Image (tube, rainbow over all chains, first blue to last red; front, side, top):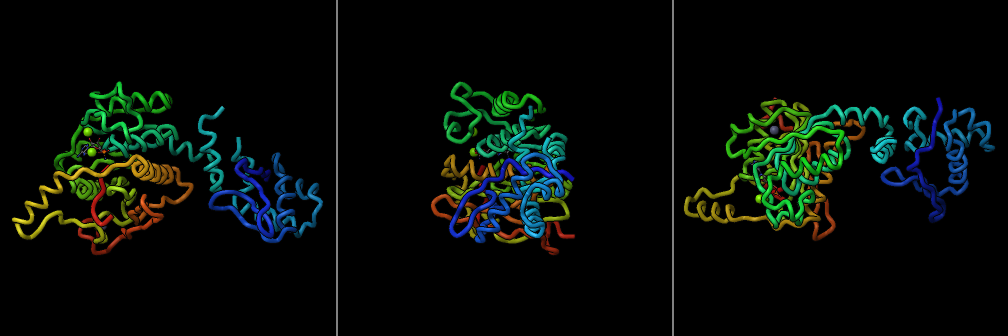
Amino acid sequence: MDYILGRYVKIARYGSGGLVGGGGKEQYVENLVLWENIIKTAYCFITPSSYTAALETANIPEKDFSNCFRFLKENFFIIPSEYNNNNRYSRNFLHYQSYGANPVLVQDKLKNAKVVILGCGGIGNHVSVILATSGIGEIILIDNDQIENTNLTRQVLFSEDDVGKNKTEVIKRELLKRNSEISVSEIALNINDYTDLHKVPEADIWVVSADHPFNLINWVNKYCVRANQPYINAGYVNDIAVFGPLYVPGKTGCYECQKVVADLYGAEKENIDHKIKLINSRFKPATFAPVNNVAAALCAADVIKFIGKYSEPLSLNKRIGIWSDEIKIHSQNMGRSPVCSVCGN
Amino acid sequence: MRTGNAD
Ligand SMILES: *NP(=O)(O)OC[C@H]1O[C@@H](n2cnc3c(N)ncnc32)[C@H](O)[C@@H]1O
Ligand SMILES: [Mg+2]
Ligand SMILES: [Mg+2]
Ligand SMILES: [Zn+2]
């Protein structure tokens, strides 16, 4: 029954009242008197204190104190003293506390988790290092490519001295330089047929950050539905950052439930079809690190939330685009269809 | 974003 003020609380005057808190839970309090009383209440909990011990020293009416305490609690501005107790993950612990979570139990779930990174290029680089430094206990890196100089625009764990080396081996070296408390392993594999997915180990979640052929995502989706394997896709369509869907067996839609994304990269007319296939074979995305990094970042966030259970991943039932040449975030609905030819009932 | 992504 001791409470403490989270370190992530800040206070400002603003407009006709004030602000309490920052981020999604920031509250504007127009009533100045109420804002002042929230501050006085907040101040009682700098050190761990009971409701009654604070009510003893607050010097405002109990009616007002009760209101202020409820307000601070319902926004997780004050948290159980239990939840605040040196620690390399301590900034992440503030993030978990700010959602009303016990940060040690979240951290324990991350430590016990295994994640597969399928594809160790732009997306894979950025996701892997976030997960490693957030304390995901076991990371499996899958790729069969070598580092090229053009990769250095996005593939942040690679240096000039690394050109020609294998991607999995350099990611592993760089991850363990950043967090030597975790386990990393490599698998040299190119999934060029559906059947190669049998070589990919079961895990808490697959990060699907590989993109050849155009229908790899379709293969992965079908395999993961059949294998009861959660996955999340991320990447970009040229200048649009994409993340999601986050597929959870029996819970969310799969990639094919809703028919929003094109699946015929071709034509019913053979002459036209061959032209299309050539153009699409020659296709190289207009990669831009900022697009890459946004997609990767929000993909990693959803992995940490999926495993840590403290807040709902954004990409459940959704494939989310963030535009880079205008201000726009748009979700494609990928909710479950009872008539999905892949995952139905 | 009506086509698949690259990554
Ligand atoms: N998006 P990019 O920066 O090009 O990184 C993609 C990574 O994924 C690897 N990759 C692509 N397709 C496959 C398959 N089918 N199996 C295994 N790995 C794949 C690329 O080598 C790249 O590093
Ligand atoms: Mg390459
Ligand atoms: Mg590529
Ligand atoms: Zn489906």
